[PDB]
Length: 273
Length: 10
Ligand SMILES: O=C(O)c1ccc(/C=C/c2ccc(O)cc2)cc1
Image 1 (spheres, rainbow over the protein chains, first blue to last red):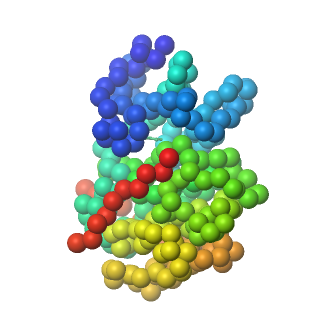
Image 2: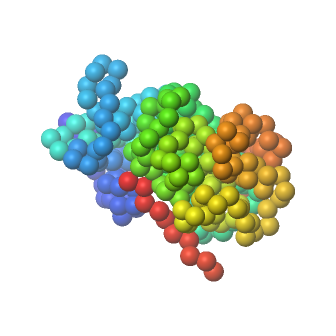
């Protein structure tokens, strides 16, 4: 029974994360986030390793739930007549990266480097576990302000990672790649790299570069803030119009701009405390 | 200053 294992608290973020409520596990007072998803609104379904029919979001969350602090951990889930309930870990204190950038403006490159590196490691963990997130954006990244650790959240648009072409997409359009805009076709890794270029521009410029379809497909990146030549080069490479011209994750992490990253604790002490 | 906003996925 859900209501016996958890003391349920008020809505978190006034619905901005979805139907997510504060909670505490009665077993050990562990803080949790309790996310509700309506069966009627769930598009993609999968099966757990035993065979039970569950939302794809649960399948993907279970696949990445092993120990790496870079992705949000699913602690348990429950099925109800009309919905599924997901028990997620709740780091505290947190602020999501969208609100962080709004309040602080364009981030210093040392801080952007630390955040971007952690996002790359978290996305690599997903792919290593057979999961494609498909909605990487600052709104879906939580910052643990005390530990300087970032958490990727919201697998509600994700899919099993495959090497063949994707013809469906329900993530965020302004982070989606031009081959999706133009042809409704994309491959998972190179589309992820495009969204990471959007995210990195967002961090060092204070907002995303493109709002309209014509900007996404046009191939021009204007820098509205002072950004180093090395960082500009990485962003423009991630935002190559043709997917085969984009870097691999290995090439991103070996890029000159990515060298000498801060540790998470160093990041918190220099930039967050 | 420019207009920065969230974008729904869904
Ligand atoms: O996977 C998801 O969709 C998902 C959504 C939301 C959260 C956490 C939200 C949060 C945590 C702590 C707070 O103090 C305030 C808000 C985690 C995961």
